[PDB]
Length: 216
Image (cartoon, rainbow, N blue to C red):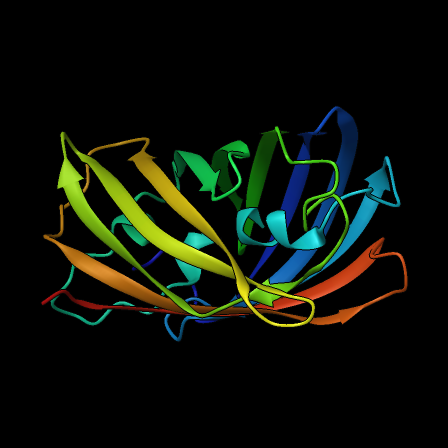
């Protein structure tokens, strides 16, 4: 898909506010876009240490690195070099809500992501503000096309200290900056893991695998 090489890097800039706490994050990532493998190294650049669970941030930190089979049009890769934007809602089980937006573009063999996040109404003694989360379970996002955009839906779960999970609904709208060949209904199977962190989570490393496939 041309503008996109077998081996790509990326820069992500993230900023936002969670329960009134302002922060900024910067990351340098790298991966194999046609293999769906990705890794990124993150630094909390303002407002650290964060008084909330790192995990709510991890999934806002790279869709062109999704392995698409030949028979499903790759909406994200096609959008380049112009790029795309998206809006996401995360609706957690205890009433907390996160809204996220992104703008993506490209500089040669390096993507640039500008991510913004607003997280409100996490209970002060809940697992997010008390840092009791221990990573996301693997998940499968289901996507369909509407008016030239992709609409995604994913029921996610955060692992908790001393067992059990904290459940979340993701709803995402992805919008390419120019018309592309539209896929049908499909889904993307992903596993996201923090592979490395320092004590206060001001330096984090993450890896993701993402694999697109037909839906049933």
